[PDB]
Image: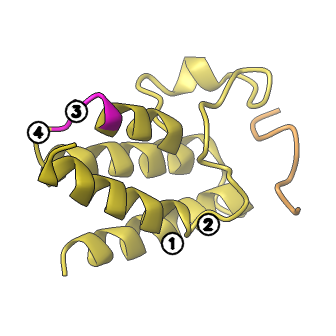
Chain colours: A orange, B yellow
Amino acid sequence: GRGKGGKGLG
Amino acid sequence: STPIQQLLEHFLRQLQRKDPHGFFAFPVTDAIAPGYSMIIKHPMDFGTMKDKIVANEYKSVTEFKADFKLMCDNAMTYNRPDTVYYKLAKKILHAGFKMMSK
């Protein structure tokens, strides 16, 4: 659960 | 605004252009980033830095560079190395420091 809700691949 | 505020706004615009996705635009929350407030003691982001320039709260380029380094450091502390977030933090920290020191 360490990490952002989205993977930031926009 | 003062000549220093104008200089810092110039640097901030060029630094934010290095983050076109806006990952550093606004404060992280624990809903977005589980446990973030247990890991990061002093959060920072570009929106907070802009409000500080507008309020005339930076005495020098040195204090402004320290907030930009705190922002990037927090991202490298919270996110794992193989993520888009840690890689961009490291990229822009070094590019942004060389830009401001030329």
Closer-to-camera residue (B66/B56) = B56
Q: Quadrant of residue B97?
A: bottom left
Label 4 chain ID: B
Give the spatial CA distance, label 4 vs label 1. Answer: 26 Å
Label 1 chain ID: B
| Residue B79 place in picture, x, y as percent | 65, 47
Label 2 chain ID: B
Which residue position is annotated with label 2? Answer: B87
Residue type, label 4:
Lys
Query: Which of label 4 and label 3 is nearer to you?
Result: 3
Which residue position is annotated with label 3? Answer: B56
Residue B59 numbered tag: 4
The quarter of the picture where the C terminus of chain B appears is bottom left
What main secondary structure does the magenta stretch of the protein show? loop
Magenta segment boundaries in residue numbering: B54-58
Q: Are marks 2 and 1 in contact (CB under 8 Å)?
A: yes
Closer-to-camera residue (B70/B4) = B4
